[PDB]
Image 1 (tube, each protein chain N blue to C red):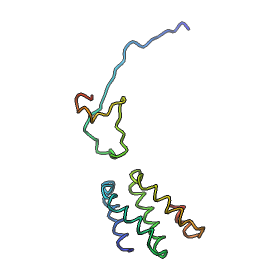
Image 2 (image 1 turned 120 degrees about the horizontal axis):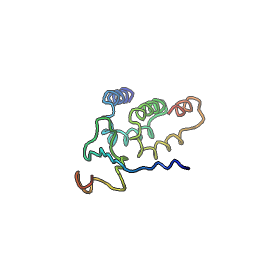
Image 3 (image 1 turned 30 degrees about the vertical axis):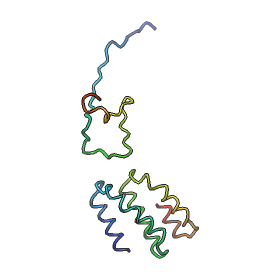
Image 4 (image 1 turned 45 degrees about the vertical axis):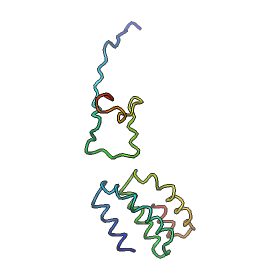
Length: 88
Length: 49
């Protein structure tokens, strides 16, 4: 998991705004992984999602309806997840 | 109000190069390219202008 996610983030950074064309393929799976992954890596996924959103800016639009729900479901007042969510 | 200077002429200079996106344009889904309540894509590059 970790190496694959890091590779995807690197590719998006290297491509620049050209990477927007890949959102229909990546996001529908990435969010599902967040939904079903183990807690040990969910925090990492939130941090990488943060960076991904930063890279794609206003094109994230159609996915916010689900991103906000994932953010609310896991906001359990645990200091670590709170810091990660606040940065996100 | 003795100073009654008035506008006599208006110059309309348009650079609406329909069909061409400058390289610094971010596109496209929310672009809402509606100008003077016209959507240029339904008419073509000359009629729309």
